Length: 422
Ligand SMILES: [Ca+2]
Ligand SMILES: [Ca+2]
Ligand SMILES: [Ca+2]
Ligand SMILES: [Ca+2]
Ligand SMILES: [Ca+2]
Ligand SMILES: [Ca+2]
Ligand SMILES: [Ca+2]
Ligand SMILES: [Ca+2]
Ligand code: NA
Image 1 (spheres, helix red, strand yellow):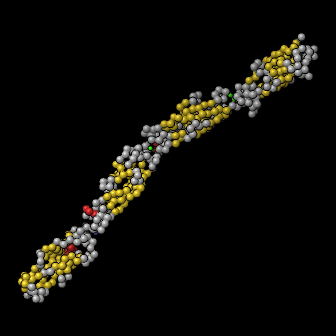
Image 2 (cartoon, rainbow, N blue to C red; image 1 turned 90 degrees about the horizontal axis):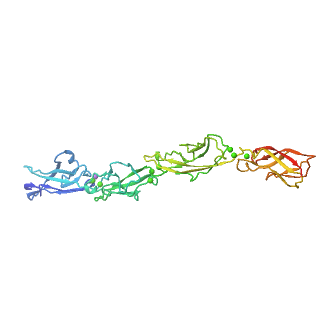
Image 3 (cartoon, rainbow, N blue to C red; image 1 turned 180 degrees about the vertical axis):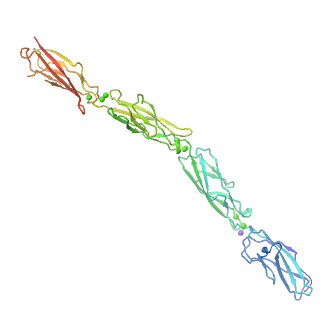
């Protein structure tokens, strides 16, 4: 051609996306002589205005002003390249037109949010007031602010239980907690870009909330009233019952120790404070006391320990043949007339067993032509065939009394009956 070789414009401000498949055309540049050339013979060329490696990411067609990516771009890597392109002429006074491209890469939500911590290992205490700030999640997206407008939702789990601020990302109790109800908690959160450019992006974290204990459950006694039965005859330091209670709480808040409040005056029972184990530790006697009932007290090991002093062990002693029958008056004296009729009461044999049941009930018997008989129950000795002094003046036999007892203890004594004149 002829005249000054130029470009329409000394400089251009194109702008493309972040990921744009290699070879993405950008600008068509055309040099133009002032006086239209018959034989315009024009080479284009290009460089990176600053650093050689920013050149390496574009190309031109030396032939036309074709300007395309030599590789997919990425904003986070470089947010702007700046290129300088020159046209060249084979004229004997060789001609150059000189121009500048400002490329500006745009974001494409290529990155997804990233949690500062892959999973959260956290812990709340129970009977803690509503809306208690438990914990706060953070994530981060290396993307333009519109592909990093983070919004945290509880994807699943406890959602009923705890609350998440969609923006703040702050876990908060939605009701008073209760460990005894609810040991541990699992909830799976989600951080979302609210991404625009291709769409949104997200990644999730598991948050493990462990509920921490508080002495809030009293220890309940296993049986309401623990009924129990001892032979008076029981051997010493012998076990009788294993009182037990349980505390729904955990750690030392469930640790229990037992102890007597009442009824074990005059020893005769010891409570092993950790066993819960009741041992007669001294002789029992049914004839002294037939029955205990002794209140028992179960205690936590908490900061404020709790207490259940509504413990009851109603004990019942059982009789044994330790006592032997024993008479009103061991010397038994009688004076029967001879003319008294048949089946006539002479004397009343009376004995007594301290023992209680059949260990008390007495069968009488006699220990020697004998003119007397004895009632086995009443202990009355009546007459049987008449007699006169001349053949028999005076009688001296015995009488023997017995328990209806397991080993039947018995005792006997003697009776005197002087027959008398009409
Ligand atoms: Ca991006
Ligand atoms: Ca993003
Ligand atoms: Ca509780
Ligand atoms: Ca508790
Ligand atoms: Ca407790
Ligand atoms: Ca006794
Ligand atoms: Ca007895
Ligand atoms: Ca007896
Ligand atoms: Na990218």
